[PDB]
Length: 496
Length: 119
Image (cartoon, one colour):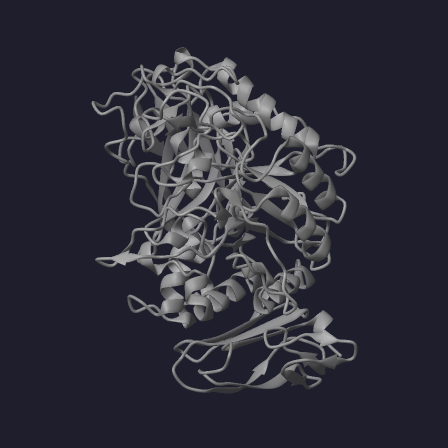
């Protein structure tokens, strides 16, 4: 429902985009569990069509051919092993549920699928489910191309085909039931909740009808009254017919205005300044905090022409991406999702990356394992932003401050700002083109604190910058606009 | 189907008002209801909503002071606003959202709203 169902005191999830199940299981044990991560959003676990032109794009995973748990990430036994191993170290699994459609209406008939199931897209045949012609919306679409021609018409957005994908007749109980049996199988395996893909393309009541069929979570890992966490992917930046509020009664909704506006402010575009973030959250017109799933970027818009366009910050803009993710993880608004990506061979032509369809690192189509090096970074083209010290330590900061109110805001009237969370954490940012040198009230008890952005508290010492907070809570902050990271963060568990 | 909004007025801080919203004329249609408000110079922001199953959502600034409920009949809702503060002053708009698509159930556009002035 609205509660994430993470283990108590864990406050973020990470999207391990296109990772294989065996690698995620290992990552839960060696890293996510010990480092306090709440959970992992996984790529669609159900069987999809194989796209050979272009060669195995990441987007083929959003074109279902059955609900069998067999993909390039692994098979059902590997998926079950991952969910168990992660739940056992306190890390939940959330599934990307692709339920609005099946594969492209133009895909060829046959067994060119990730588990070898047969399908005949042209004749609306999906025997592995099973689905047939009457289970799709072709008869409802009022457009001439069969596609969505105007986003100011909710009926075409919900009933017509999204980029040529066969649109499921979600008002039918048979269809609502096939989808629920799939989600309930995942709940039985131990999943904690779901990202409902392409929610704007479904009627609010049809999604609720499917949700009404879901069981409570598995009692080997969750208390008996527990409803699955639901976050609906609705892209609503304003100025269109469909609003994110239409879905609030079903569960949380992705707040895409968050990353779009934060990226514009952090880049200092369109006259925006960091000092304007004093009233960040509902004051900027966003949805209620208790209904929001927030993030700086996602797998679609980190490619540059998604929701937010070029203002979206990504790992390619690492210096500013870290400050945006750090501000997000320190601020109380919303439930936070961090991104973990792969690097692809970009190829710009006339200013555009024509290679943005490229799928995960692979050897002849088999996804590469995630290798871990000693500096704790990753190999094999995986970026592993969730392992960057500055992000890992801020997800720990958000756990440490859980519940504490936004407090002690300061700004220099331009792009230097700071704020705390009750008496448990404080963060300071310098996004101006000059030195930050200020005495600030931190709200924290006096002591010597390790800055968790530049280092870590190890034993009774700090490996980075030390911040000396006096008994009245004040501390001297000095941050160069050219520092490795132009922000500092300290909290109760970083005190010596 | 027509959108009918009512209840606006001027009360002093601490007073109450109750807004009403109805999307009547075709009982086969089902509309979920959500109120937004626009103060001069601010944007039109969500404040409270309720779906057909009675599930409520409130923005934090009105929690415990505003109560949204299903009205007299299907496709009707009320927004009981108590302990009004001067910052609650704004033009309020009910936006009915179609819950299920059906032949001849229209999408309803923003209406004119109602004016609420506190103090």
